Image (cartoon, rainbow over all chains, first blue to last red; front, side, top):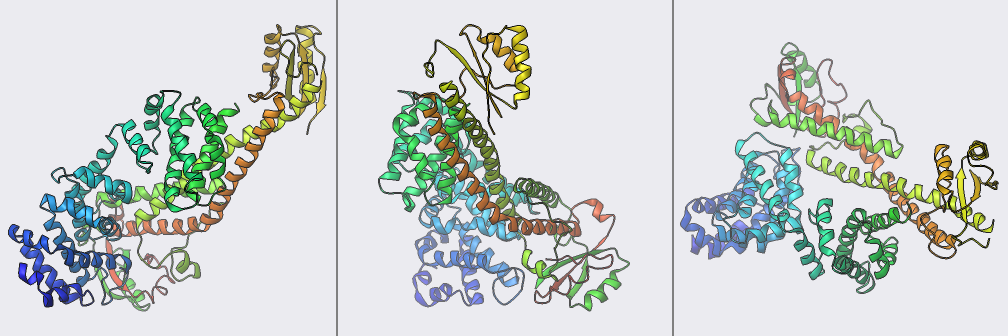
Length: 318
Length: 312
């Protein structure tokens, strides 16, 4: 197995995806050896070569239709076997906890696509397997299970995706079970961090991102008190930080545009809640900075900016 | 090619087979649907039915706001020009439509409450602009505090008389009554700084806005100077709101009809298929068949005499 994997003529056949029949047979050959524990170790050495080919097959699967039964991958006999095997192959090697942590951190971008396949397909063979692999990495038993949940939640927005998935149950007991378990783990891990801690950790890096508790009002209410150290010094920190981003490093370039929209969202929530923060915006000069974002391009930045202006405004005149 | 789903009772199974036949349906096999466990009576479809009721509510709420009224009687066909255009011949993914309506529902609720809060404050401050200017000139106590003035708006000079009548009966002739015509009525009472509360009681009971000092914005010297800059924030912040709302309105009007047609069509599939026990003890035949998509058109032309040929 280990030699044949390194060796060229067989591995070439498997890289070609054009010829579904040949490729299918070869992927199955390997996945069956993987049902046995020992082969998993040699197979994981060669992961780099075959594993982009397998994610490509899932990607192809996503862009084509399902409302015909042409020669290519659809939801035909041929297709139903190719998807299943690819996924299954993944799933097998994921049984070893260390491989799974590694697999998400390298392959992250490619990894996120499994959630998509779960929607588009109505087939419990495809759906089930996709749900299980993601589950296994999010399990406690994977070391740095925290890390993988973080990458998935922040960047890839895994959590909202699961909440939709949960609604559409398909007939298969085990599927329903996997989906529910995964909903709990994702949601629980991020929220359960202390509120002040997450905000400040983001503040410090100047690498603010929306997250489930920063669009939630409750987070802000508990945290108002934590800021007060010289008239909401931390709150003033976020105001300084926002002002700076617009003016230095310019506005209207991509990096600076992610931080702004999030920051304006965060400020809005504290002001609606607290009437005493209006003073802080005036002293700092933040009051001015809001007015500037309004004119600026990017729809999402302008929405958040408008909501910030209105929050100050409601309080000035009673 | 594309799955088509038909329901009838077994009685017009033959009558159906021939008509379907003449239109270009192929691989016509009568079934039940237990041989497709997900697309049979189970909890799963019943949850989908709820998901569509939520969809229905969201469209109606968005149309109300937009001042565009519901179009109904429904296209779900693929015969029609519009049928092809506003309903894709492909499959439906419930998840996508829920998420699309979610984002728009959330945006509107912000937009609608924000227009009303911003707008009300503006109409008042523009009203109290002229009021504080006129009232200071009526002078040598414009930024005074040892004299009490009562500035106030009142709907009309008629309502103001009734106030004058209370005052004269119950407080004596300690007022000087002046009035300026607006577009409203500027009324002015002028009093001591220790009889304020008694004047206030009259003002509250006849619906007047006679405050000691009008506005919460007073803070520059003159009062008006602060008021005039705060009126420039109000005007431009309302306009930006109106633009975001307008933009989005032109963007989604057309989209809402298409998702509405799509969602109707999902309800119908579930029903055809049997999503509850009642559909079962009313029609017991559910058949399956494959229709090429280049011919999808002709099947929808005749909706079916007591047959549903609404398909995917």
